[PDB]
Image (spheres, coloured by chain):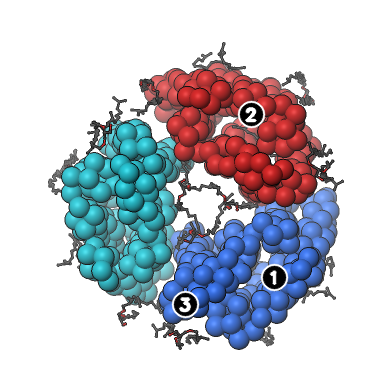
Chain colours: A blue, B red, C cyan
Amino acid sequence: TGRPEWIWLALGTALMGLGTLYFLVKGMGVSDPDAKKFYAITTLVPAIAFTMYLSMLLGYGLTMVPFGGEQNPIYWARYADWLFTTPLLLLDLALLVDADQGTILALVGADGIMIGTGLVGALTKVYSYRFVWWAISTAAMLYILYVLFFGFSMRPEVASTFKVLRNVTVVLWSAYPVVWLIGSEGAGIVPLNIQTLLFMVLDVSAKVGFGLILLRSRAIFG
Amino acid sequence: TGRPEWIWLALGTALMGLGTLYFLVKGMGVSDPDAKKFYAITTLVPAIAFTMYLSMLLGYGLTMVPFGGEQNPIYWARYADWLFTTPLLLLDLALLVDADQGTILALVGADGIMIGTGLVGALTKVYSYRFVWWAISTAAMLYILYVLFFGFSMRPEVASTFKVLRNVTVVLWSAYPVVWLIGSEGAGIVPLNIQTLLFMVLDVSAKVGFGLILLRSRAIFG
Amino acid sequence: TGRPEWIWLALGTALMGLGTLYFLVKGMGVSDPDAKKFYAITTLVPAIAFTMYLSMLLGYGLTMVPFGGEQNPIYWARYADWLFTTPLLLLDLALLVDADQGTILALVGADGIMIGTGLVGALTKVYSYRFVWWAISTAAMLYILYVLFFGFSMRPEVASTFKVLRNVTVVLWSAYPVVWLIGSEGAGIVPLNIQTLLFMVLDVSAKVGFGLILLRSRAIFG
Ligand SMILES: CC(C)CCCCCCCCCCCC[C@@H](C)CCCCCCCC(C)C
Ligand SMILES: CC(C)CCCCCCCCCCCC[C@@H](C)CCCCCCCC(C)C
Ligand SMILES: CC(C)CCCCCCCCCCCC[C@@H](C)CCCCCCCC(C)C
Ligand SMILES: *C/C=C(C)/C=C/C=C(C)/C=C/C1=C(C)CCCC1(C)C
Ligand SMILES: *C/C=C(C)/C=C/C=C(C)/C=C/C1=C(C)CCCC1(C)C
Ligand SMILES: *C/C=C(C)/C=C/C=C(C)/C=C/C1=C(C)CCCC1(C)C
């Protein structure tokens, strides 16, 4: 449309759809329950992102938030996406290393707080307070990153793939608060179309690229 | 009230309440954890539907969606219902056959996508796009139906009851996209009061009738 | 601010933050998976409440509901809080006594209905109907309380601590429908600032005081 960010929403929709179908079909012929768990998780993530990208593309997942005086376009739908897909991603990680249930609950819960406070910050109409929600969310994120590094005798195939995904995770997820901060969501240094670009590249890498790495490894098979 | 569909919301409220109390009391005197699981799931479903029917009845779960120019009455509350009650129903099925966790996650996730895209379609103000959400939702549904048929040495009592519920499920759930499509939610061929009627008959059959069948079987006992 | 209830939202924010950090740090040095489960659950609860208190404090989690003619301030954010934190609290209880999965689902589900109907009642614009939602919610509550008392050979350390928390639970949770009923949410007998006070004292006691009791016991260690 007339939304210059449309092309990135379009590309994101397509690439999340294609990764969904790739992983869906790829997961055809899997019988191992454990592999089945990662296929389910890992196919669902871009499946959900596909729907939320499409909802952004079609304009459904977009709202206007008054702040700085202005009517600030906020694609709220990506938080609906992340609300489900980031814990699923963490679940992929958590299951890989067979985390304790307490640790998984800590991660999912901290994740829900990260996304929920990010959404609150995204929709907050007092500009200064946006960054307060950003900060708390970032602290939840740093908590999660902490746990992924200092809280986790697995088979070497698990380890190796975990350590790759874990590095992928930390590098990509850490970029999101920066994009939010510098983008139209936060301080407005970088335009919406570029923030949308950045998040789409991160999301495809964090969802499809992550899943390609994961669904490639024998780590997912018992 | 003046809502001609009220009587069906009224009847649905009553019948979901009565089925809730029937299953609640019926489940009094159950000690087997497994039976306890199906009683919990199966009582919760019409309990939730009771609340959402009442919310529709009282007008709370109703909104107006602009499309075709018009202010289209949309009872959004039934999606809040379904969001919780359809995965629970699938969980009843999944537990019956002791599904793999991956398969359950696939079902619940596909279900959330079915309902969430149905809700997005229901609230979408671009009329043509409504049916795009319908189509994706329908594809999630067909995925679920696929899985219920081609993805599931259980005791013959499990099998038999599973196969009955599974047929009940497929026939009733398949009717909902058709009702949505032809009803005021979709193409508007059939009035809101008749769509509300149709969904109430399906919902009572899919919740109370389903639960009667299930809570009747010894399949639910270990 | 000019919201006389601000001080209580401020105090609640602070005390939930401080309890979050206390339990977070306190939980440093825990390795027992079971203890890890209660630390996770129990730290998350005031962590979530911290965010929702702050959201109330900052004015984000506040809406106006027309009823009696008036624009009635409703802090909806505490229902978002409770939606997650009350099942977690019940989960703390449920895990303590190793409840059956069916019973946990019954509790969480009844809880979701309690909070969801309380939120519906809170946002309902027909004043009389508010108390209908109150009544149903109260019945869900009484169901939960029923289950906590008549539905649960645990080690004596479990029992004892369970029985204390269970009494804490019943006494504190029972006060909330009364506060809602007499407060600005319900019949308006007691002002918003006092209802906010009352709920803050209950919430801190039910979250931090509860968690102090729990995270003090050896009941949480296998
Ligand atoms: C087996 C594979 C590679 C899967 C292909 C199926 C569908 C597409 C997904 C694969 C694409 C990219 C891999 C993930 C990493 C990323 C950095 C993607 C960034 C996307 C940018 C838009 C267009 C660029 C492309 C060259 C993919
Ligand atoms: C043991 C039983 C049958 C349960 C009775 C408790 C409460 C009511 C539920 C039972 C009713 C119906 C069975 C489910 C199937 C359906 C097709 C119901 C359609 C409902 C239509 C409205 C009025 C019709 C009735 C004759 C029930
Ligand atoms: C080890 C302990 C006690 C924890 C301290 C960390 C942070 C604060 C939480 C402890 C405070 C209170 C215990 C819970 C019980 C309550 C009745 C609290 C009611 C709060 C009222 C506001 C100010 C009062 C205080 C004296 C705490
Ligand atoms: C699938 C998409 C992924 C993996 C998205 C990850 C997003 C995050 C790690 C976002 C974190 C944010 C913060 C730490 C603070 C500001 C708000 C967020 C939500 C952008
Ligand atoms: C308890 C009620 C039940 C079992 C409801 C089931 C509803 C569905 C199977 C609905 C499916 C739909 C589609 C496939 C597309 C259009 C939207 C829906 C949500 C009506
Ligand atoms: C953390 C906060 C806690 C433990 C809150 C508990 C709240 C309840 C037990 C609330 C119950 C209510 C009813 C029974 C009816 C009216 C509405 C509620 C939600 C206040």
Against C153, residue A51 (above or below) is: below
| Label 1 CB-ligand 4 distance < 8 A | yes
Disc 1: host chain: A
Query: Neighbour class for label 1 at 10 Å: few (<14), some, many (≥20)?
Result: many
**Type of the residue with mark 3:** Tyr
Which image quarter holds the N terminus of chain A?
bottom right
**Which residue sits at x=26%, y=69%?**
C2
Against A10, residue A201 (above or below) is: below
Element assignment for label 2: helix
The quadrant where residue B118 appears: top right
**Which residue sits at x=65%, y=23%?**
B194
Disc 2: host chain: B
Q: According to the image, label 3 marks what residue?
A: A127
Check chain identity for marks 2 and 3: say if they share one. Answer: no
Element assignment for label 1: helix
Element assignment for label 3: helix
Q: CA distance from mark 1 to mark 3?
A: 26 Å
Disc assigned to residue B192: 2
The quadrant where residue A24 appears: bottom right
Q: According to the image, label 1 marks what residue?
A: A203
Relative placement, left or right, of A126 versus B85 is left
Query: Are discs 2 and 3 less than 8 Å apart at CB?
Result: no
**Type of the residue with mark 1:** Asp
